[PDB]
Amino acid sequence: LSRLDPPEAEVQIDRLITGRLQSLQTYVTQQLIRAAEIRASANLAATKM
Amino acid sequence: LSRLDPPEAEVQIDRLITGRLQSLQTYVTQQLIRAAEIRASANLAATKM
Amino acid sequence: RFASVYAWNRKRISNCVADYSVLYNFAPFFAFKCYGVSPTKLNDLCFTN
Amino acid sequence: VYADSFVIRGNEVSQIAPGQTGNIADYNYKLPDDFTGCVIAWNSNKLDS
Amino acid sequence: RSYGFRPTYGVGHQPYRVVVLSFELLHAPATVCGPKKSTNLVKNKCVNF
Ligand SMILES: *[C@@H]1O[C@H](CO)[C@@H](O)[C@H](O)[C@H]1NC(C)=O
């Protein structure tokens, strides 16, 4: 923002917003699978109890 | 690279890198689900044995 | 003499070695705008006509 | 800050740019591919010819 | 080789005067600076530095 004018600032930061969104989505995508893996073991432990 | 100067080569190949990475991520995303599907059947087979 | 717009002429160039750095001395133009290929490497390519 | 100054032909003004090659960008003055600066050119026909 | 700058030549062959300004924006003790006025130093409070 301090080196480039707004007409090109909105183009430069637009290449960071998409990258950071893509970086953030993979985290929840893998957590959604680890949660199911944990839930299966929780159900098995409840049955064993 | 042989038809465009690097100023525009780094813009042209930047549109291929992102597409190929998006193509590559879906493969592992689906493999991570097929693995759990197979693991369920493996656990069932172990119990049956 | 140059032909009028409504009767523009077309000249075919083939079967010769083309050096594109010599036409700079043939006319006092300034821009030399190209669309499908960078003017830098026009000497590194082979065309069919 | 570093200031460089010279006199060229109007044809080759477009060759003072990163990634460019030609008669004047090969054997006389070549800019780096990662240039960060400004280029200023003006006509001086009334006092240099 | 020498130029032939003369008033007869049109645009694209007339002499041009070129000046290139080169900076470098890295983390190091800076000497040349723009015309801005410093203020006092405040501490332990949320400010914009
Ligand atoms: C154009 O052709 C004429 C006649 O052949 C010649 O006198 C003149 O020097 C040529 N100019 C260029 C730029 O080739």
Image (cartoon, coloured by chain):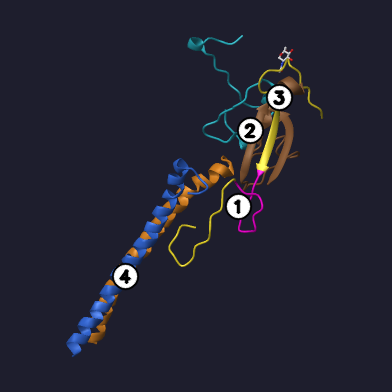
Chain colours: A blue, B orange, C cyan, D brown, E yellow
Write down the residue under mark 1: E25
**Name of the residue lying farthest toward the right:** E1
Q: Amino acid at mark 4?
A: Gln
Tell me the quadrant of the picture where the N terminus of chain E can be found.
top right
On what subunit does the disc labeled 3 rest? D
Circle 4 chain: A
Residue under the image location 26 percent in, 74 percent down: A36
> Where, by quadrant of the figure, is residue B49 drawn?
bottom left
- Say which element carries label 3: loop
| Residue C4, horizontal then vertical, whole percent | 53, 9
Question: In this rendering, do the residues under marks 2 and 1 share a single chain?
Answer: no
Query: How far separated are the C-alphas under marks 4 and 1?
Result: 41 Å
Residue closest to the eye, C35 or E14: E14
**Distance between the alpha carbons at the discs numbered 3 and 2:** 17 Å
Q: Badge 4 is on which residue?
A: A31
Query: Element type at marker 4?
Result: helix
Quadrant of the image where one finds ligand 1 = top right
- Residue designated by label 3: D44
